[PDB]
Amino acid sequence: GLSSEQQRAFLAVTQTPHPAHLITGPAGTGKTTLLYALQKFYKCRAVTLAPTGTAALQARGQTVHSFFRFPARLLRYRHPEDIRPPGPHSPLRKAIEQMEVLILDEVGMVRVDLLEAMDWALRKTRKRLEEPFGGVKVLLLGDTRQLEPVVPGGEEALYIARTWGGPFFFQAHVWEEVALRVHRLWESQRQREDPLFAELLKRLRQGDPQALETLNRAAVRPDGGEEPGTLILTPRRKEADALNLKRLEALPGKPLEYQAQVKGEFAETDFPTEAALTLKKGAQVILLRNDPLGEYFNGDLGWVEDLEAEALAVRLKRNGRRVVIRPFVWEKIVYTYDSEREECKPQVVGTFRQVPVRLAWALTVHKAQGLTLDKVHLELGRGLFAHGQLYVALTRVRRLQDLSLSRPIAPTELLWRPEVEVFETRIQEGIWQKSH
Image (cartoon, rainbow, N blue to C red):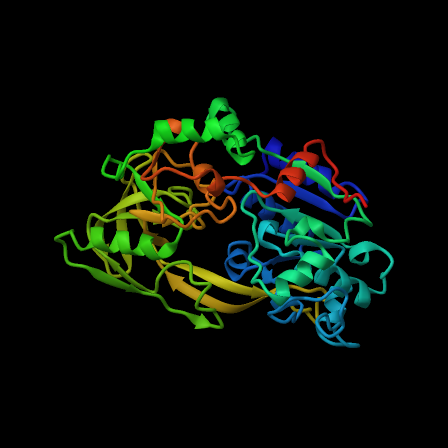
């Protein structure tokens, strides 16, 4: 069930001896089903890995650090003190010396030292320490805009500045050895781009001053979140929960707590939704899972109508109330070699059981990633000039008319980092390889 756009990438990456392939493009269905077709297409030829627990959950894979027993600190270059190879006959080594393909979702947040750990770990155990990754066909994924890995400062920042120069996944010295065939999609909705707004976003990423004045003198509207169907996006999830709470304690209806059943090993930070979910009839809520039948979708903004102990009815914004949702089961997955099969065969270690819905009067930009939204309102916190971290917020809409920021933006909150502005544009032909 693959469309021509998803099939073109599938066939372009699977039918070639080239190991390194990057697939760019925004989040959403079409991108997920592309991975769900890839990982099932090989199905112990490869494993699916991710930098963060959240990414590993929504990608059916294992955390990189947890798959490789990598320690939660700066991974020094080819250092055996940090990158310890699994010993002989160990029940990780036998499974890693099968992985012809390695899928890697959300490469935006993969730090450089983390990528160079994977390469050396794959080389010093599959015996292919000359070829990059031990020959393993790496399939990188994720919009390269929802990037910028945190670097603490002090000792760790200086070492990374000296070894690589920056924290990005492309500054790794692996790419000085192999070429990265980049299949960039950016082609899911032609005119719900508003090509003037796309060029406006590109001029903001390049520091243009008058593009910034244009953005401010068309979209600045204090508290323009009172207009109907306005989702008040916030950068930080602290004020988002605070905004949902104050709008939740306005509803007269009696609340109902939905209790999650966290079975097995499931980290607290990996929780998709709050386990003590207080809901009232009339709350703006959003779905977090696609319906196996096909009635509702992931990211479907609804309104609570009825509150049953193990089900709830929501009037969808998209078409009109049709579906009652039933608690979904999230599984923590770890890839450990199967004895009988002689082939990795991943394993369910954790379980999270609650209704796939969360409060949606406000949302963190992180959780809002890739959602097609009709109308948004941005909440400035006077400190978000985190070297362009607010660009990801402007991209959450297709036309300038839908966005309404509460306070003006400084030129610095949107300006991209110089190393990024060189990567996004040297990949616009195709293959990318690091010179000198």
